[PDB]
Image (cartoon, rainbow over all chains, first blue to last red; front, side, top):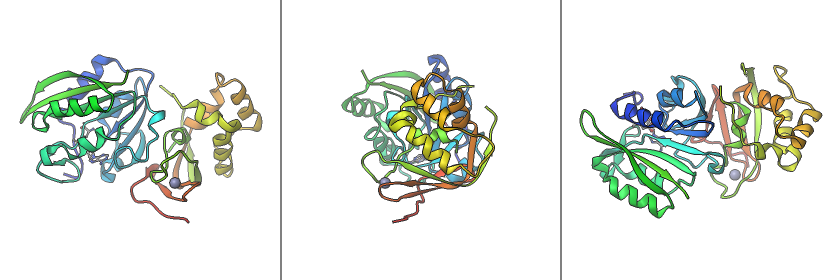
Length: 164
Length: 122
Ligand SMILES: C[S@@+](CC[C@H](N)C(=O)[O-])C[C@H]1O[C@@H](n2cnc3c(N)ncnc32)[C@H](O)[C@@H]1O
Ligand SMILES: [Zn+2]
């Protein structure tokens, strides 16, 4: 695939975001791909959308586009919320979907760099959601599993993280 | 890229905040939904970032700011109708962002800010 296309996983993240009613924030849509989540977010927020995949950015629904590797080029002090449907697929290092060992390599890199006040992260059962929660706690985030949903292939967990 | 992004981007090499300086090959005006920006980034040093942007875009006449517009915004940041219009109402399609400390360059190509495939200038 040239870029990651909207799937049941993305729609469960979108459904959870919808119920939260995020409004009046500066939101980073990390791994925006072609911007399906950005499209929903920009209705109530100012959104910066980033991806490693230039092809997806070049066919983006539209927004404020940055090609970047996670958050290194982002000033996190300026961002209220980060939303991330990450490459979570175990045992591949495909640049779009691959999460390598446990499907957790990008997730783990993200958790160890994230400092914004609030985050929404999607994970699957194979990533070991509890280890993700734990790592987030270690980073100062109070966490909770906003939503669990079985989809075609696996079960999706939406993690909400917030600093006190 | 719209200039409000200058409140959100940073050099990925320097471990402290630095100033990213804009070079603009071409820019288009954009119609001015939610427009929130990091006001403090544009107020500090008497509106340094704004002055920097105004200089970078001096050959672009689609939209404009003035000494006064900037000074007054620094006074009353609550009155940012003109600032928002400048920061959200312009899109740099072709250009560059340069870290003033290490000279790292982020090309801007087709309005996308490229922070992965960088250029050195020092
Ligand atoms: C599973 S896809 C999610 C796409 C989209 N937001 C959605 O929900 O449908 C993960 C996305 O992260 C991007 N990605 C992979 N590694 C990245 C990285 N290191 N930094 C930023 N984005 C990355 C991929 O290109 C891909 O678009
Ligand atoms: Zn630098």
